[PDB]
Length: 303
Image (cartoon, rainbow, N blue to C red; front, top):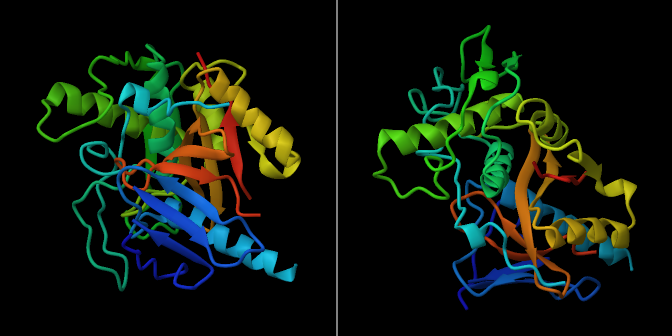
């Protein structure tokens, strides 16, 4: 084992990670093994959606101080998307340098975890074939990366998505046919969720995702947002288990000051660990506990 120096907000001793990989807490008033995997490694540098989740474990363990098997559905189809090239080839191009930050002018903004999570689930279903409704929104007045005013628009009602061209994953030297297909999908999805574009891109998430999947992309009326706080632990996990039992990956997110920090839950080991795809090409994917004890999910995702 080779420990990772989490640093940042995970630079304490309340949790330790060693590269597969393993995650163990540092206080027996909380579960011992938090997350694990037999392949790849774990990292959170520059990956805010993974770090946000980890930061919740820490808050959880500190709170403890006061005291079916489903094979990864995405892996089964070889779905591994990311947030940068070529997935973001059609997101807005950064125009301004944010005071005090290094310049990203000329680069396409990140797709956003919310859009990457949503796109992977859509690819799993290879749906829809035809977009249903257009979408527009105005970029946040406080966004320091673009000139204002800025209105974004996606002609989704005119889309005929070719799922043979939208590949399950991208290597790098794919032709325009394939790169255009995935970048168009990512740009449409991001716009449908009012993405606040930047070197990192944020969206409110769940509330936007459930509405976009039905209104813009034609998914089943069964699609809806569920909040963790409205369910008992048993009912919550039973919801997730039912989705997975029906071959329906789940959109999941935690909340930060910049919006939803999303990922996809697409499997279960049977020991209460759920398989997670962080949308970063594969790094850090594995089995995690929903908690180590403002989370939400979008379920009922199917055509």
